[PDB]
Amino acid sequence: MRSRPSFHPLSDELVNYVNKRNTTWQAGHNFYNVDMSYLKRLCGTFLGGPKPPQRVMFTEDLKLPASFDAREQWPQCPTIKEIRDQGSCGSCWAFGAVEAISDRICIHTNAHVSVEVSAEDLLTCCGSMCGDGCNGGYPAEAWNFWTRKGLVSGGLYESHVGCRPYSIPPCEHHVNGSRPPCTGEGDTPKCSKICEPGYSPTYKQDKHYGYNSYSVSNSEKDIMAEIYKNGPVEGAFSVYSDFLLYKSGVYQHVTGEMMGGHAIRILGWGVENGTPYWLVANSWNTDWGDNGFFKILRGQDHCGIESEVVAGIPRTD
Image 1 (spheres, rainbow, N blue to C red):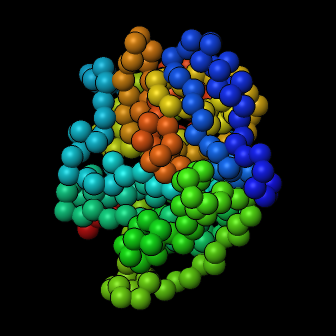
Image 2: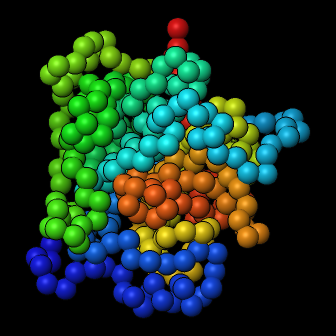
């Protein structure tokens, strides 16, 4: 870490070049203080990892809306609106999964059950199967663990919600009053199979399993139909430096180096000022981009957004 002198990562020069570019989005400084280390620990998804066995498709001329938003479609599912924070840990491969899973539980058991699945449980109990914890992982294997061992409930940091709420404090940037500084130093907590005190049922009793898991076929229409009847899904794309600068509009890479891979939740689509896009939920807290969400160019496999999408259906009784 660079103690306390010259803070802030990206130059106003990058922010200004993107803005001078006059593209479909506007740049702004999302990060101050943060060490360059932290910014890389944020992109914790390995692209081109293992794929799920299956791959679904749709072969009927479905009539899908011009725009769509799972939050509107499913107003009764509180988790669909929620934005989570991964802290100084590359657990996004796990976040995109538990988030989409929380949504699907509520959707597929249509209304009666709404729970926040533990990203913690996943981050800590999958193991080498999923990759290397806070240093990165693979989305496909996260869903895998859901099918095999399932996941328990667990909300936000210090929320007292669920069996295992996240134990990694929010580093929603910093600046202000020396809040937990965003650092890249952060181990992966251990797989503890015990619910937080003052919470029934028990850990193996509070488990939620998924059926199988699959890939959506790298087709705009296919990815759209899937979300339409099954709910949000997990995806991953290549994060370039300028992306960390997002404020609003439809993001289109214009400059910067590839920071790495990053998994996210895709919950809808639309068109804005003529540019087709995906409505995406990031996991860098709600004081980033457009309240935790952002839009990215759709229909051109931009930065790999359409390349690694996966999901699965939930257990139920």
